[PDB]
Image (cartoon, coloured by chain):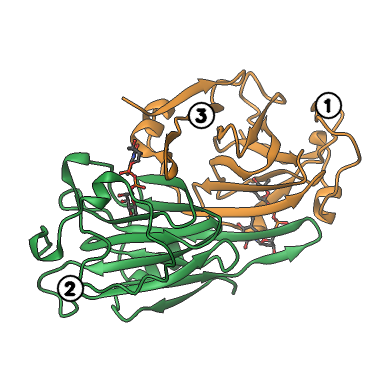
Chain colours: A green, B orange
């Protein structure tokens, strides 16, 4: 059968997916999501209630974001360009608390990352432009939104960046990891 | 509140959606799906179990497709280029049986179409290339796949096409509407 390669990252609950793309003389076709395969690799049920689509110029960084209530599990990919995509483990009781994982996702490699509730998430744009799409397990709730600053010295994330990133003001004003609201 | 304009088409159960795109100096962001708004405009619950992504060159036509068992309701859009997107009512007992609706969907207008189970669906590519994404209420089942030929004379679909379309062989070999398996 044809489906989707699944790899658990250094932080096992983070999973990297890679789809099969079928070519023919009209162009191509692939399954960007399949609930049977996803729940099989995930090991538990999931419902996605919202899909999001953003476009960002080279050097833009969005993160590090989470919702401390109505927490959102996220399945993410890029359909134009390339990003470096990061997950940070904010579960105090996890043995990988304060650790992070990062992978390059692009329109061309078509790779995806599953990021469970309990994590902060961010990405930075490496190409001229990038369009970034993702599905979430709960709805947008601004009152519950939190942020950790991208260049926190305790987290020490190895961003593959050349120039200083462009950020929203609320991302520039992100909290230090030591002062941040974390999960159990 | 910010959300998604909804319009019922000439065949009322077909719905055209139009999202709000928020610009800022990083680029843009929009909600491509929201279950609260969708089920509110739809008037009933829906679960999507599979997402699909295809790329096609100018003049390619894919259709007219349905699954007679494990029938798939479809929510569709384009993220690169422009297509003419068509829904045909195949419910024998509907007063709009044998009728169709069509709209232009593009990367730029970001409009979407909801096509319930009971309909055939097709599109044709109007730009150099088009990438077409959609979410479905059931899984792929080849044994149940059926096709009606794009240029059926009873259906008389007004394709905005210049040259003869490029088709898969199984689409070139599609059934006449008069000989096709239909829904109740
Ligand atoms: C997150 C979100 C924003 N918006 C609107 C509010 C703003 O006007 C505009 C941009 O909001 P921002 O919070 O600046 O978007 P953003 O792209 O900086 O935020 C996102 O970043 C990702 C890295 C995270 O994984 C997401 O969970 C989310 O935090 O979009 C929605 O309508 N729905 C949403 O779900
Ligand atoms: C439809 C489908 C195809 N495939 C594979 C089988 C083939 O190798 C390749 C292309 O198959 P095709 O049937 O030629 O794809 P297609 O793009 O011609 O078919 C699609 O057309 C849309 C207009 C309809 O709304 C869809 O319901 C579907 O019928 O993709 C999947 O893996 N999963 C799927 O769900």
**Residue under circle 3?**
B17
- Residue A79 lies, in percent from the top left, at 55, 55
Q: What's the distance in space between the residues labelled 3 and 1, CA to CA?
A: 29 Å
Which labelled disc corresponds to residue A154? 2
- Residue A156 lies, in percent from the top left, at 25, 74
Which labelled disc corresponds to residue B41? none
> Please, is residue B124 above or below residue B92 in the view?
below
**Residue under circle 1?**
B154
Q: Pointer 1 indicates a residue of which chain?
A: B
Nearer the observer, disc 1 or disc 2?
Answer: 2
Q: Residue at x 79, y 28 (%)?
A: B157
Q: Specify whether disc 3 shares its chain with disc 1.
A: yes
Q: Secondary structure at mark 1?
A: loop
Left or right: A23, with A133 as reference point: right
The answer, for residue B89, to whether it is visible in the render is: no
Q: What's the distance in space between the residues labelled 1 and 2, CA to CA?
A: 69 Å
Q: Nearer the viewer, residue B54 or A97?
A: A97
Q: Is mark 2 within 8 Å of ligand 1?
A: no
Q: Pointer 2 indicates a residue of which chain?
A: A
Q: Tell me if mark 3 has few (under 14), some (14-19) or many (20+) residues whose alpha carbon lies within 10 angstroms of its own.
A: many
Q: Residue at x 77, y 38 (%)?
A: B126
Nearer the observer, disc 3 or disc 1?
Answer: 3
């Amino acid at each position: 059968s044809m489906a989707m390669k699944a790899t658990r990252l250094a932080i096992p609950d983070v999973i990297l997916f890679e789809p099969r793309v079928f070519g023919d003389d009209r162009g191509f076709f692939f399954e960007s999501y399949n609930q049977r395969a996803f729940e099989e690799a995930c090991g538990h049920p999931v419902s996605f209630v919202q899909d999001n689509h953003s476009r960002s110029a080279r050097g833009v960084l969005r993160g590090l974001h989470y919702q401390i209530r109505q927490a959102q599990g996220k399945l993410v990919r890029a359909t134009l360009g390339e990003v470096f995509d990061v997950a940070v483990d904010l579960r105090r009781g996890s043995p990988t608390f304060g650790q992070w994982v990062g992978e390059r996702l692009s329109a061309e490699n078509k790779r995806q990352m599953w990021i469970p509730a309990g994590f902060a998430h961010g990405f930075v744009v490496l190409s001229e432009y990038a369009e970034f799409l993702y599905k979430t397990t709960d709805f947008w709730a601004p009152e519950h939104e939190r942020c950790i600053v991208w260049n926190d010295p305790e987290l020490k994330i190895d961003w593959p960046l050349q120039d200083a990133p462009l950020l929203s003001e609320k991302d520039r004003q992100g909290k230090a990891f030591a002062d941040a609201d974390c999960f159990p």
